[PDB]
Image 1 (spheres, rainbow over the protein chains, first blue to last red):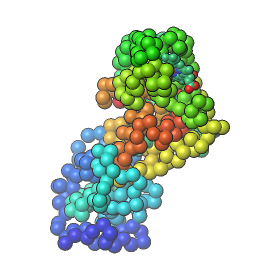
Image 2 (cartoon, rainbow over the protein chains, first blue to last red; image 1 turned 45 degrees about the vertical axis):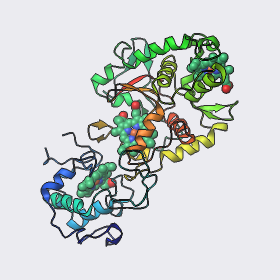
Image 3 (spheres, each protein chain N blue to C red; image 1 turned 180 degrees about the horizontal axis):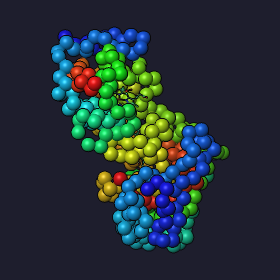
Image 4 (spheres, helix red, strand yellow; image 1 turned 135 degrees about the vertical axis):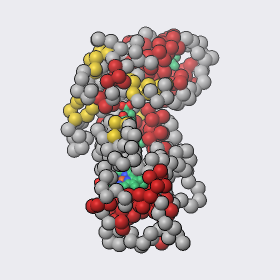
Length: 135
Length: 261
Ligand code: HEC
Ligand code: HEC
Ligand code: HEC
């Protein structure tokens, strides 16, 4: 199954303990999604020494993030980083409402109809699986 | 690097670092040109007009200035004189409140109102090559002059509107101009070195697209790249943001046309 964005259970710390999909997290595919501007765009802000070209320095290096943070905290950061870091510049990847002039990707066009999350449940679990190896 | 002097053609001293304007002193120690955030190779392209590709377009606009256009049979020069004199200082003080309009005007809106109402000529596309090259000419004859846009009086409510927009998060990525340019200036987004997002160097010649880029063009692309809907070029929103962003660099020299990534 999949847990829809509006149906996610988030605790008081912004932690999400249950996965968004029960399909297994592919650590190999999560690595890929992080370099794509069209998906995660994680590199634009974050260093991952493991990936091995021009990572950003807005966000902290993600080396060893699995060693400092619970999986539930890592997923939570990806569902809605603002729950975990208030007023953070990190986009909210599993939010579908509460935006201001959202557009369809980088097309400058207004979204008409429902908002799809920046990443799917499967894409988030792929990326979570991959971050969990950074110990 | 960031602290090396910018002198253009051996003659024009550019103030690239200045005391933060009082309205902004909260946030920065110091305001800086986007030039101070560029590589040495890119920085060098602005040090000589012969090495500055934007100046090719400024040279072509010099001809346009003197060429009669529209049904009235008149050229810019027929009312404004030599461009070096008639446009001197003007890039430094716009956007500004204009009496005949009872509104803050940009340089483009002034250029278009001359074309349509004084020249009998067709409007230029706000961010098209014709407008951007003329605006670059205008800027270039006031290089080394301090940007000094009024933020008070009949300009104030427009300035406040632009201020609101600067700190408003847009798009599905949910970012304001300050998100990146105030909080994270001097950091990297990928290979790009975050500047303070100043407009004193505009129109910019960008190595990315090998052309001149209008202020509202940049602004459009900035909101777009939050995964957002940009305001229209020439809109009251972008006019207001331009006055406000301009005010963020009061004291920096005029640099247009500048060379950037
Ligand atoms: C050729 C396309 C041009 C360009 C690039 C500009 N002008 Fe004119 N100009 C004229 C008058 C009477 C004004 C004042 C208008 C008002 O108060 O509304 C202007 C104004 C401008 C500006 C702003 C100047 C300033 O000092 O603030 C600019 C940037 C500008 N113009 C550029 C008169 C004329 C003409 C009389 C027949 C002609 C032709 C032009 N201008 C042509 C041009
Ligand atoms: C707009 C910038 C931005 C982007 C894009 C971005 N991040 Fe972040 N991220 C941050 C910042 C800044 C922090 C630190 C929290 C803070 O102070 O805001 C952070 C924190 C984190 C953390 C917690 C790490 C720590 O040590 O604090 C993780 C894990 C993380 N990000 C992963 C990701 C992933 C995965 C993506 C892609 C889906 C991503 N980031 C995209 C800016 C960004
Ligand atoms: C996603 C992060 C981000 C946001 C949000 C953002 N920018 Fe930028 N901006 C950049 C990057 C990266 C550059 C290129 C490097 C630099 O800053 O010179 C840039 C460059 C600029 C420049 C060019 C500066 C120069 O010297 O030529 C201007 C002007 C600018 N931005 C204005 C704005 C405005 C106005 C907004 C709000 C609509 C905004 N920015 C929002 C990332 C951002």
